[PDB]
Amino acid sequence: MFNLFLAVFPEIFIINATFILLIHGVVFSTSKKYDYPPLASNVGWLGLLSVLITLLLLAAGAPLLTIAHLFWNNLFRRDNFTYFCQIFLLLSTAGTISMCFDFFDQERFDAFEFIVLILLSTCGMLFMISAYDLIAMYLAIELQSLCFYVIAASKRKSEFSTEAGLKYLILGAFSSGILLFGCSMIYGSTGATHFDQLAKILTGYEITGARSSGIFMGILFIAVGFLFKITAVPFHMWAPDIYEGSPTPVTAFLSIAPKISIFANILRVFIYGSYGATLQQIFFFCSIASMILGALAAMAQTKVKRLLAYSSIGHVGYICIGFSCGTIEGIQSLLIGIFIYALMTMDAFAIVLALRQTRVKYIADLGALAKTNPILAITFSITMFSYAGIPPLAGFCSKFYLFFAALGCGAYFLALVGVVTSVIGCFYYIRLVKRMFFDTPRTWILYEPMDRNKSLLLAMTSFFITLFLLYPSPLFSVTHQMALSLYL
Amino acid sequence: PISATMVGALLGLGTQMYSNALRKLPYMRHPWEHVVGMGLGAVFANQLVKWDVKLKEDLDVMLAKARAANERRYF
Amino acid sequence: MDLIKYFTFSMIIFILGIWGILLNRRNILIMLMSIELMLLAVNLNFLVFSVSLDDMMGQVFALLVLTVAAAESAIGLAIFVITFRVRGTIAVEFINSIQG
Amino acid sequence: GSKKVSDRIVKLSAIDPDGYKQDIIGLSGQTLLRALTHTGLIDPASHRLDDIEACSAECEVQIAEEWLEKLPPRTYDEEYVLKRSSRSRILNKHSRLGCQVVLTQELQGMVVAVPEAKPWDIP
Amino acid sequence: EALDKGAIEILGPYGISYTFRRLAERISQLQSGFVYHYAFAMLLGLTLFVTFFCMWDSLSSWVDNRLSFILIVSSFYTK
Amino acid sequence: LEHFCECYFNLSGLILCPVLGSIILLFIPNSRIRLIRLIGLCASLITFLYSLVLWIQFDSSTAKFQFVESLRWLPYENINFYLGIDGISLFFVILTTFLIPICILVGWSGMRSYGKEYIIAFLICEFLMIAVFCMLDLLLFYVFFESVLIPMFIIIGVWGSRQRKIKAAYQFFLYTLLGSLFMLLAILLILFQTGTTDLQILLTTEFSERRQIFLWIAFFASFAVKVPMVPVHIWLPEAHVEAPTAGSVILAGILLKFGTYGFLRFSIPMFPEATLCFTPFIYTLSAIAIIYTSLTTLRQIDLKKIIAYSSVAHMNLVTIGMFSLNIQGIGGSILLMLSHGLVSSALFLCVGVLYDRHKTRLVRYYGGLVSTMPNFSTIFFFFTLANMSLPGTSSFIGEFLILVGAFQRNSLVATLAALGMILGAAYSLWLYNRVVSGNLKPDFLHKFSDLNGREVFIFIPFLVGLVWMGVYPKVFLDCMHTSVSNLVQHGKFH
Ligand SMILES: CCCCCCCCCCCCCCCCCC(=O)O[C@@H](COC(=O)CCCCCCCCCCCCCCC)COP(=O)(O)OCC[N+](C)(C)C
Ligand SMILES: CCCCCCCCCCCCCCCCCC(=O)O[C@@H](COC(=O)CCCCCCCCCCCCCCC)COP(=O)(O)OC[C@H](O)CO
Ligand SMILES: CCCCCCCCCCCCCCCCCCCC(=O)O[C@H](COC(=O)CCCCCCCCCCCCCC)COP(=O)(O)OCCN
Ligand SMILES: CCCCCCCCCCCCCCCCCCCC(=O)O[C@H](COC(=O)CCCCCCCCCCCCCC)COP(=O)(O)OCCN
Ligand SMILES: CCCCCCCCCCCCCCCCCCCC(=O)O[C@H](COC(=O)CCCCCCCCCCCCCC)COP(=O)(O)OCCN
Ligand SMILES: COC1=C(OC)C(=O)C(C/C=C(\C)CC/C=C(\C)CC/C=C(/C)CC/C=C(\C)CCC=C(C)C)=C(C)C1=O
Ligand SMILES: [Fe+3]
């Protein structure tokens, strides 16, 4: 009996460690004897340790995660794809946590519950990746969402943070209701919620004239929920406001991990299921809309956070092009784009968090940065050029596959749109470089140097961004492996 | 020649220096950290090369199974 | 005709929630209430289908969805409370400062 | 010494959101925002540059038309910032961006109303 | 003056910059800051999804794809 | 397949030289200005000598690629990349390696404020441009060309003289990136047919007349922006004027040549039928550019603006030559490319000598400089003559060989192209006489200094090269004929 639970050792450990940290934090934060010490950094270090131990347990027990698969079948499904997805999610959570300590001590954000909520949301996203039934998927999505709602409003006396939370909760709850409605329609039409059963029922028919309008609209509503989650246009406008109004570590965490988890879900639901061309057209139209609107709106922005939010919207458009074309290379390119976008976003938010110690808000606040911190201005410039997709930086991979998918599938309008939006993006990315290197403002802002954690993370992500295309084989192989494991 | 150990050691040393520079510290502020970084970089690079070999090995079998499943169509 | 009548009941509840979103641009509390109405309609959809299909999966998920609805309302009303506390008012013109 | 700071000083009066009138001091050639930040009437941390690209109307002031005729007319960008920063999205005809008003000797005695501070410190 | 700094600038960097600035301006204004607009947009997107992707069976008798995309673009030139 | 070459001096080490210089300079404190200056200068000079050696081991009888060596990207070996040169690319490698030390020398006096970033940017540019000229693969040609945009952007924006450098840099980056994206689209369409981007294979595949038309247009959209051809030439005056002196030298002398190199290297041999179909189109565009841009040059009031507009007329003559598709045409196009790279660079250096002292580009302020700067006046006159294609100078050889090539194909295009002899003389002599001749205007300028030793030394190799190519172009043409001949014949078998 005990050995059956080897399939959930990683999750058991992280949940138990989260409980231990909750108890530790609440017991000593309330201690008069110890004079109510702030425990955000102490619990943060212990939680980083817990995340790393979870990663060790998961990575080193690759075969064991598939033990007792028949017993666990109606609860979740662990395979090669979920293996690598969960590893990448844990690595992202560890990096995001490591970027938070200067924020904890200098702002004096003393709430250790922040770390606990991050860990519980990580548990939720882990269960999201392995979900193999509509019920499990919904429950894990809701756990993740509720944790985000709470942490988005963590600055509870701030107008901005409270506004972010309110908008997030209302729009999140609305989208979740729409998705749940879709799930109910699919169950009513097919008598099934398990992904295997849905695959068997729906395969071979798609729209064979006598199409289940119940099945067709259930798929549509579920897709609407998914598109809200990935911040695809027109279900996107929550994202810029929430990203700007939340505390910056929250914004960094939301920018990466939920995308990993929800794309895992989207792959395993749609790609593994079957209504077909309709849904790929959904993601097609939403990709084009996201690219255009992200480019234009980002061009309008004068503030750093809003610029990065709109940039992420545009990039999810680029990524969803891969899901749309419905090929093994499409899935592989989508995974490559997520990995690279995640490492670039981690780099960018490490810089943003470093600069938030002097309250960076506007793009113009970067003036004369090439004088006051030359190596920081260069590092940030490499990130921008990578965001623009200039070769041979890592960001060039997404542009290359965008045009690779258009030319082959025959999509000349998509290629047109990609060219235009890439040029617009390059303009608003090099505007930052111009501000740091070319401008001569009358008043300068002198920034405090970053802590060791962010400097090390920045140093590694900056080598990756510059040097990835010298040795890209492991990512290429691992992502081809994952794309294949979805069906075999 | 240019071995994974040497590339990794150079990358680790560069990482420590880049980290010091980002913090506006002298390049060689804590030299024992430079030694630690060279060691970790060498270890990382060697493990990445071995992992790459293993990854290609697994992808080979998996492509083989995909090809067999596809070829079953023409039976 | 039973199944079409049970489904249109839940359907009118869902459409009422949608209309409540549409008609309450100055009243975000009612917007939250409309979202609960939609969640209730979905829950009813699972229960009706469970009976019609003679299957228990609709019933397990209905209970779990009730748990989600409870947690959602708790957290949402907390966020409403803190927004009101910061502003002293619930009017929508005082929660429009993030834009662009 | 034939060149004094007194040669550039511009006498000003500011009415705080509570309505009380205060006599403040600024240099000619510098912005109204700087004069207002000298005594903390506007928080200097909320508006650190004198550039329109780093402005969310934290510098906004209200000036009667007798002094408005003595200023250059509002540019399109200024009105854009003022209107979008308005809670009701309405452009106040007596509103000026303090960071865009350069003090001169001709503005001696100008009366300025400082509205209640808007939230500025993005999490 | 008529070509290099005239027509080629207007149907080039000068004109392009002008139009893309005005359009980025308009798209930024859609992010109005009102939660009601964001919910309305989601409802409109959901309605669009149902309408185009399932209720375009009979439509085709009255409707053409040409007119669809023409009226879309034409909307840009309103007021 | 490992294509490793026997030769000791090869292409990879010449790639590595400025890279190593840049890494070393990364770590040297800005207080050690002398060390930074010397290290950068010496790295550039060693690269130049290495390229000279590469010229000696060159074999002028084969139509093949030489020093071919290979470069292996994945263990799967599906994608493996090759470097190699021929008689069309050799002298461009040499010109790049020669110009970079000149750029380091021009900023010698201001290096205390320039810093190591200036030298590092120029060394990185050198590495990227040599790579571009040495690539036997469409996709890496793409990757290495776009990469130069970043350091060029930085060079223009940081060390440009005035705030117009902002707009100039934006326009340079955006125009060039648009063209580059068009050619990326072309590269992917080719890859879908062939499954490869290796230049040698594409030279041996057959493209449909239809597929050739589309691929040619997509190549043209990059290359015409690069050349530049009208009407996408307007980025060039802004960028080449607002850049610092060495930045202008690199822009005019090397970066402009990349479009004509792309025409010579991929478009003409890969799609000969499309090349034939588009020849009247290219002839018309180039002839319009020569006449209209020369006449615009005549009415410019800024020194740098006059020299920058002159380059548009010269490059479109180059395009006429290369699309004539015979020995005179292609040989003259290559020779004029190299000669322009020397002459326009020297002219930008002359204007920079004037601007460093007086800080104005407006012609009206100058005048009568022959009486205070006779050495500068003489050197300026020599390069003015070279820019008019005076026989005896290097530019005349390429100009006349291109007119020969064009006349044998179409007498009208040769006739329109020979009008350049009249218009270029007009603007060149007008510029020279308004700057150097006449009386001084002491109310504008009253203090003067002729060239120092560094400036004289900088000018010496330009003079030597101009005269050397002008009087004995056989040294260059002998190393190029086999490659040029095989380019002209490619696609036909009679
Ligand atoms: C070719 C790529 C495509 C195009 C993209 C180009 C992107 C860059 C744009 C080029 C234009 C010019 C760029 C100028 C940058 C050069 C100046 C520079 O970065 O110098 C840095 C140097 O920045 C670095 O630290 C770079 C370190 C990266 C390490 C990479 C090398 C890896 C192996 C080396 C092993 C160690 C050294 C071996 C020899 C001792 C000095 O930084 P500061 O902020 O001035 O001061 C730092 C503080 N302190 C000196 C006291 C320590
Ligand atoms: C994609 C191809 C486009 C060009 C097609 C060929 C040419 C067709 C005919 C010309 C079309 C554009 C006509 C523009 C009329 C002038 C509009 C105007 O007012 O000009 C303004 C500038 O705007 C333009 O000229 C528009 C430039 C358009 C250039 C092309 C648009 C963008 C194309 C690229 C993006 C889309 C790519 C699609 C690719 C298929 C000047 O601004 P102002 O405020 O000073 O005007 C005051 C006024 O004169 C009264 O006093
Ligand atoms: C792939 C491209 C090439 C990459 C190059 C690879 C080379 C390997 C790297 C070599 C590293 C060189 C330096 C090693 C010596 C430094 C040792 C750290 C000292 C230490 O204990 O640091 C503590 C902080 O932790 C820290 O600062 C450590 C945390 C740093 C964050 C990184 C790890 C986070 C988790 C994983 C992130 C993954 C993200 C990817 C998605 C205390 O510091 P202190 O004593 O100065 O006091 C700080 C004030 N509180
Ligand atoms: C074999 C070469 C490499 C070995 C490195 C040591 C052995 C590996 C053990 C892990 C080392 C990781 C890096 C340790 C330092 C991490 C960053 C600590 C910096 C910090 O903020 O806290 C400092 C603690 O010092 C410290 O943490 C250092 C405490 C003493 C360690 C230094 C001795 C290293 C021995 C190197 C070879 C010795 C040869 C004989 C065996 C207090 O800083 P502070 O106030 O003390 O002063 C600093 C003057 N800026
Ligand atoms: C045979 C027929 C064909 C033959 C060829 C004819 C071609 C006609 C000419 C087309 C080429 C145009 C190339 C575009 C370059 C635009 C450069 C404008 C940039 C510039 O200098 O001003 C900026 C404006 O950027 C902005 O705000 C605007 C955004 C940047 C512009 C990029 C948009 C281009 C996208 C693609 C357009 C063409 C489609 C291709 C099919 C700065 O402005 P600021 O001062 O306000 O900024 C704040 C300052 N830091
Ligand atoms: C400057 O003058 C003015 C206008 O002009 C732009 C206006 O009209 C408006 C605003 C009114 C509008 C445009 C309402 C329409 C909003 C919609 C459609 C909500 C959808 C959400 C967004 C943000 C747009 C994105 C939607 C797309 C791209 C379509 C869906 C995506 C796919 C193709 C799958 C105002 C106030 C105005 O004063
Ligand atoms: Fe202001």
Image: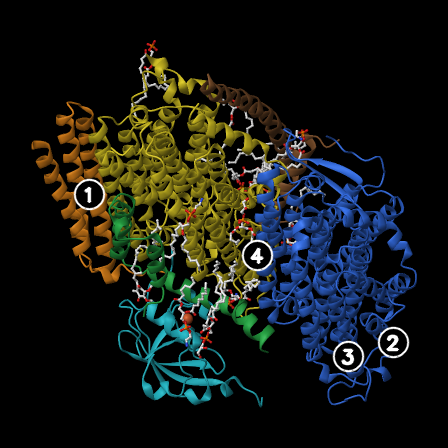
**Do dots 1 and 4 share one subunit?**
no
Rendering coords of residue F314 (x, y %): 74, 66
Q: CA distance from mark 2 to mark 3?
A: 19 Å
Disc on the earlier residue, 4 or 2: 4
- Establish whether ligand 5 lies closer than 8 Å to the Cβ of label 4: yes
Residue linked to disc 3: F426
Residue linked to disc 1: C73
Residue linked to disc 2: F378
Judging from the image, mark 3 belongs to the subunit labelled F
Q: Secondary structure at mark 4?
A: helix
Can the viewer see residue F22? no
Q: Colour of chain E?
A: green
Q: Nearer the viewer, mark 1 or mark 3?
A: 3
Q: Colour of chain B?
A: brown
Q: Colour of chain C?
A: orange
Q: Nearer the viewer, mark 2 or mark 3?
A: 3
Chain that appears blue: F
Callout 4, which amino acid? Leu
Q: Colour of chain A?
A: yellow
